[PDB]
Image 1 (cartoon, rainbow, N blue to C red):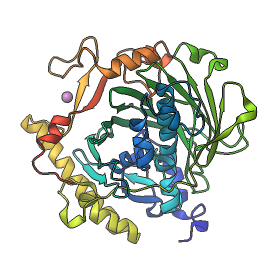
Image 2: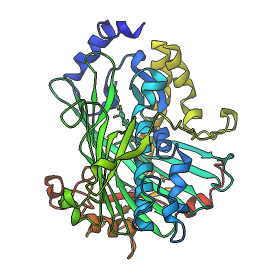
Image 3: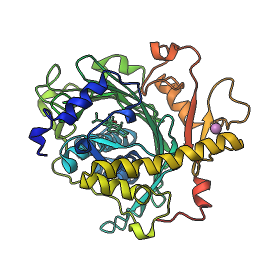
Amino acid sequence: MDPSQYASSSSWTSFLKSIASFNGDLSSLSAPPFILSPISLTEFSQYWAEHPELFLEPSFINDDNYKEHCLIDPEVESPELARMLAVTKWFISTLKSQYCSRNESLGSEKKPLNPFLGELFVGKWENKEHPEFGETVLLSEQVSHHPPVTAFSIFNDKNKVKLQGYNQIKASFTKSLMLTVKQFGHTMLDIKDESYLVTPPPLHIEGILVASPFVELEGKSYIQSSTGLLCVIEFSGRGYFSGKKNSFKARIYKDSKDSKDKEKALYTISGQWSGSSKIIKANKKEESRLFYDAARIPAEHLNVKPLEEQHPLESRKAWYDVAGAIKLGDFNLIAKTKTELEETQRELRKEEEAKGISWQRRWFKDFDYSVTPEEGALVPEKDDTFLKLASALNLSTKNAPSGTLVGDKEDRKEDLSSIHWRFQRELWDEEKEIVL
Ligand SMILES: CC(C)CCC[C@@](C)(O)[C@H]1CC[C@H]2[C@@H]3CC=C4C[C@@H](O)CC[C@]4(C)[C@H]3CC[C@@]21C
Ligand SMILES: [Pb+2]
């Protein structure tokens, strides 16, 4: 049917009624075929680097050229600060990819495919137009199904720029049908020997009543560097803090201590992350400059090998029949293909439980950061990067919502674990079957 018919359709009415009895498992929502996406969440990891030049820019900034690598401020105080500005621009540039891609390609936000345990999604940005960039690899793996957890790593060996992180969410509906989503997990970006800890923001899904879902960000995201510098990004929508949706305000401070006082902000960036934003240095509000305009820079999608060459664990290969049925809008075929895949998985889980076997993750392992870790789990190292950056930001190391600070209510939750997924480059190095 035409989208204009969605809201009043029998299918949507039945869907809204199913929300009243939502059990907490988003995948249980009786969503109609017209609101289904043929893309698996394991693919979302690619959204961290769809602007190759911004992802790698920090690596080209050094003590001898930094003032030539800061468009908004040729008089930038230091290379560390020039790099923080670059990392911040990169972070902002990821937002349109992360939260607006389906609106563009599908017509609105839609229900993504719930990944199966073990699912993989790999590819690469060849950056053929920029030989100095080199190849950038994406590795994404579903390390958990109950609950859904996706781990990933994007790395550029040539320029020593590497990123790793993981993601999971917890969602609930308000009485007015707003879908509140809390993100969990974090992402770390290494630029040579300099590190950055990034925490995703919470969000809500609007437009459910009118059958035109869309993401709006809220709360805050942090970018803590090993240089001490810290960027605090606050999100808002519609009004309240800006006459336009998808708005944000980012402030860069010398350190976590200074972030307590907005007046100490070295720079203040404001605008829409899905559009244009300006930046002001210090308090010189009369000298704002364009920081980033999402509309001027088209996203660059990674190269994925043809289906014919994909391993059975690769997302698109495994979900092929389901994606095809979804595109066709065949109610019975969607139910059939999805059940076939998910039932086969349930069978595997039941067998493992009965045989005393456990699924082994391929390129990621879960490290127990608890003071009293499980006796068989891997534990972090002395100079663990997450530990030092979290300490600098005074960020909770527990499995609390992304961005939770030490002492916050969420951090004071009793019997809360501290297990985090980590990329093991060695496992990819010795990979014997998967290729790009
Ligand atoms: C019809 C619709 C209400 C079905 C449910 C859709 C959904 C709530 O599952 C979707 C809609 C928006 C999706 C989010 C969009 C963007 C991201 C950023 C990515 O880095 C991690 C996944 C994450 C956080 C998605 C999780 C699943 C979400 C939240
Ligand atoms: Pb384990």
